[PDB]
Amino acid sequence: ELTQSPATLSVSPGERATLSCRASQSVSSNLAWYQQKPGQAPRLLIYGASTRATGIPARFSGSGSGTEFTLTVSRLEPEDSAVYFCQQYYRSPLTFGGGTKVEIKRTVAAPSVFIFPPSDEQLKSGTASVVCLLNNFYPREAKVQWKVDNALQSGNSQESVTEQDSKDSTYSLSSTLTLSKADYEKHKVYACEVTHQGLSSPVTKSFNRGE
Amino acid sequence: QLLEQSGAEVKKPGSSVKVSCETSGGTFDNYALNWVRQAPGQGLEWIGGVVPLFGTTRNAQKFQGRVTISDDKSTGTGHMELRSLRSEDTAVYYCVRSVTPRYCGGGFCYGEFDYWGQGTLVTVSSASTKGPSVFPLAPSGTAALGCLVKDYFPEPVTVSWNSGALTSGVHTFPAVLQSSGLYSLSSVVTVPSSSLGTQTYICNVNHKPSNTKVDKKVEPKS
Amino acid sequence: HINSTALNCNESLNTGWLAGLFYQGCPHYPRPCGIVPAKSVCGPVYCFTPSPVVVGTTDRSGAPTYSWGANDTDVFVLNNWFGCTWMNSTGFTKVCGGPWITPRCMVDYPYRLWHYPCTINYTIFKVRMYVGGVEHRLEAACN
Ligand SMILES: *[C@@H]1O[C@H](CO)[C@@H](O[C@@H]2O[C@H](CO)[C@@H](O)[C@H](O)[C@H]2NC(C)=O)[C@H](O)[C@H]1NC(C)=O
Ligand SMILES: *[C@@H]1O[C@H](CO)[C@@H](O)[C@H](O)[C@H]1NC(C)=O
Ligand SMILES: *[C@@H]1O[C@H](CO)[C@@H](O)[C@H](O)[C@H]1NC(C)=O
Ligand SMILES: *[C@@H]1O[C@H](CO)[C@@H](O)[C@H](O)[C@H]1NC(C)=O
Image (cartoon, rainbow over all chains, first blue to last red; front, side, top):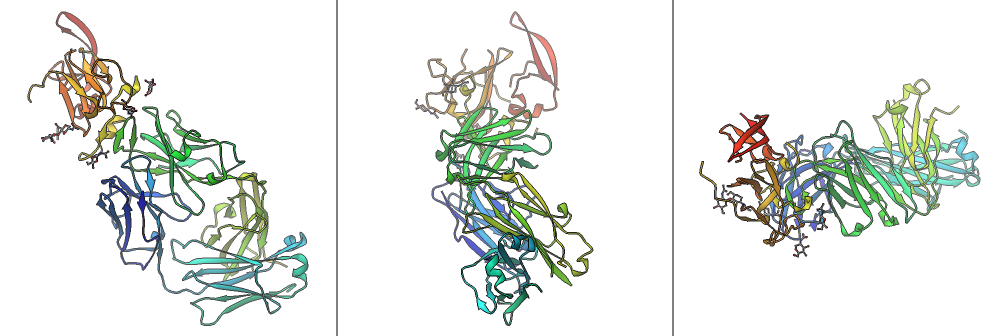
C-alpha cells in the first residue's frame, strides 16, 4: 500500500516540485509514476522507480528504491498542473497511491465578471436560472453574493469551479441563482457581487428584468 | 498509441455492464490488458487483468467472481464485463495495456501501464435517466456567451462549440447536483464583441445515457 | 498443458529481455541434462530429438504438474533427445546436453529468437540430416 503526502502542493513556475511516495513494505524498484491532467486519462511518466518513459520531458525525474520514492519536476510550467499518482507492480494486488494534486502558482488575476439573465424559453417553463460568471482569475478563492432588489440572497444558489487551466493557470467559476418564475417576476434588479483578492473593491454586475 | 473505449453507461443495481477497448490503428505488441477505475472524486483502483498468450487472469478481491476481462488478439479489442453492479461501482473505468513485462509468477506477468484508454463513466443507480434542457446564455472588446444544460441524469454530458471549430476560451464547468437529484452545468466561451450578431454560435450538447444530441443557437437578445 | 510452463521471470539487471516471451554484443562443453528445478526457469523448455520438443513441468516421479512451475516440487526431468535449452529466471539462456546441427545451422523452434538473439538474421530452410542411423526432417536456421 502506497502513501502520498502531502495530498496537495502549490508551487511557482520555474521552481522545482518534489513529490513523495511511501510504500508500506518493500516494492524494490517496481514503481511507476503517472500524470493525470484535468479531464484526461493518466499518462505514464516514470517506471522502474527512475526510468523516464518515452516522450517524457527530461525535467521529470524519479528516484528511490524499497519504500521511499520521489518524483522531481524541475522548472515547473503551467502544463504541469495535474494529479500525480505512484503505483507499484512488485506484488499482487497492484496498488496506487492516493495522488498529489499540484497547483501551479501565477500572479494574482482579477475575475472578469459576466451576468446572464434567464432565457425567455426557460422562464416560460416556470423556473428562472440567473448565471454569474467569474472568468480567468487567480487565486481560486472568491466570493459571490447575489442581490435581488438590494436584498442579499441565501440558500438559492450553487457554484461550480473549473480545474486549473493548463495554459494560463487560472480558474473560472459559475454561480447559478435558481428561482421560480413567480419569484423572478416579483423583482426587477438582479446583481451578483464579486469579492476577490485581485479586486481593490467588489465588482457588481447587474441587469434589470425586461432591460 | 491510442485506446478508444465505448461510451458512458448507466445501469440498474444488480445488472451487468461490458466496456470495450479498441486500438485506433491496428493492433500492436502488448502482453497484458488490465482495467483500472476511479470513483468520481477519488483516486485509482486496479480491477484485474488478463495475459492472453497464457490465458491467465488476476482480479482484486472486491471483484472476485463478478468480473471477466478478455482480449481479442485478432481485432485488438479488449473487454471488461462487470456483473452484480452496485452503486459503489459508479466510476470512470480505464482500459490499460502494457508492452514490456517486468516480472512473471505463475502464470501471470506484471509491469508498468504504458497506454491508457480515455475512460468510461459507469453510473449505477435506481433513478430514472433524464436528458437535459439546453438554454442560451446570451451575450450582453470581449463578450461572454454560453449554454445552460439543466436537469439531466446521470453524468456525463459533453459540450462542444460550432461542432468543434471553437475551442479557445471555452469553459465547461463541472456539473452540480441539484436538490432535485438532477445535474446542471454551464458551458461558456469568450469571443470578440465585434463578432456578436455576425458569427454564429451553436453549442452541441451530447448526453449519451439518454441518447440525446442537442444543438442550441446562442445569439444576442432583441 | 499450457500451465505446465514454468513462468518464474524477473527482469532484474538486464532490462527488456522478458518481452521476447511474447514477441520479438554478438565456448565450453555443456554439462549433461539432469533434473532442473522449475523455480529457476522462465518460459518453455525445449529439447532436441533433434526435432524440437517442449518438456513440461512434472514432479520428480514424472507425473505432470500444472502450477506454472511455482512450487518446489516442480521440476524438468531432462535426462534421457540430445540436448535442451531454456531461459532462466534472470534472462540467461541455459543449455544442457545451443541445438546446432551444423556449425552454421540451428534447429528452428518458436523460442529460438528469444533464447539465441544473435541468430535473428538467419534464414529458415527445410532440411534433412542423418542422426545415428535415423534420417530426420526438420526446419533449420542458417547463417
Ligand atoms: C541465471 O543464470 C546466470 C548465469 O549463470 C546466473 O548468474 C550467475 O550466478 C552465480 C551465483 O551467484 C554467480 O557466481 C555468477 O557469476 C553469475 N553469472 C553471471 C553471468 O552473472 C543466475 O544466478 C541464474 N539465475 C537463477 C535464478 O538461477
Ligand atoms: C491449468 O491449471 C488447472 C489447475 O491448476 C488445471 O486443472 C487445468 O487443467 C490447467 N489447464 C491446462 C490447459 O492445462
Ligand atoms: C526480482 O529481482 C529484484 C532485483 O533485481 C528483487 O528486488 C526482487 O525481490 C525480485 N523478485 C520479484 C520482483 O518478485
Ligand atoms: C504450490 O503447491 C501447493 C501444494 O503443493 C498448492 O497448494 C499451491 O496452490 C501451489 N502454488 C500455486 C501458485 O498454485
